[PDB]
Length: 179
Length: 173
Image (cartoon, rainbow over all chains, first blue to last red; front, side, top):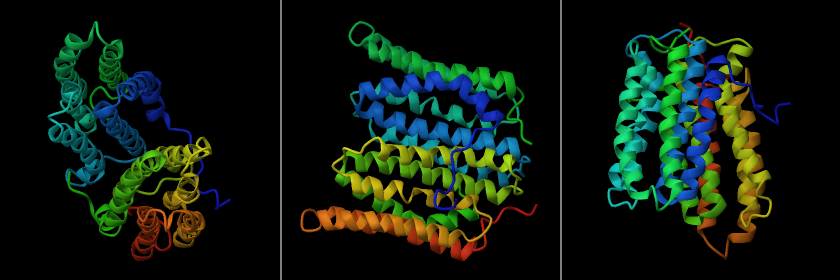
């Protein structure tokens, strides 16, 4: 029937593989972000939308021929706007009580842009996760023996990019496999 | 970073209704703010699918459903929020959104997308009329919220009529 509209659909193989690797880190990161609240919670919602746009692009690639140099930026404009949204939130909230949490995310979120690389996407995400780790090391120093929910937040966030590296390694090693 | 023709034409029509809806929802807060963030996410996936349609040759059956699977998940997330928040002080605001959000599913139809979105707008209108009955003469922010939300689907219909009147136009090459 038409009144029901678009029913829930099963994800194709590219996204199924992505979800099996990234579901548990993403869920834990979203749980701990809600527990911390404030700016950490607001930022996680933006990261979660970035991840949802990551899956939408993987689905595109599984059914689409890689377009011309210029024509690809038209496909990546939705994910690059979301990456910038996550970055400008940190830039506008420099007075935040959770600045290092905001910095860990803004300085690593560009990892979602691995889909724009035709060579070495894995080392790119490793370098992004090294930047997240610098700021998360500060969160650990401040909260390791004060608030354990911040310690799990750090571990949960960093494993998103560790699990993204495992996904790229298994399926898209030499770059996102376009149709 | 810069948007393609399909999405730029969408933004020309939907940027101001969407912004107004998000600002009013934040003013109301609570469950209305929570729901609007889910609607904004759905609208972002809509744009992503319009960018896919501009550069991609139309897929058949299962290949097409694989493309639509991200947005279908988000539409359902908007719908399950209302079904799980029946004890809400903003139940009609919640109902207005969940009974109309399937308008984002127009991208799946092979014919007549406008009357489909119109029917979703009729459902939004039934419940927004209950928000108006209740909150006009109480708080005019709810009146501005209704006007903002209904105009999203009014401007969507103008986008469909102008560019994708017989169905979503996919790339021919």
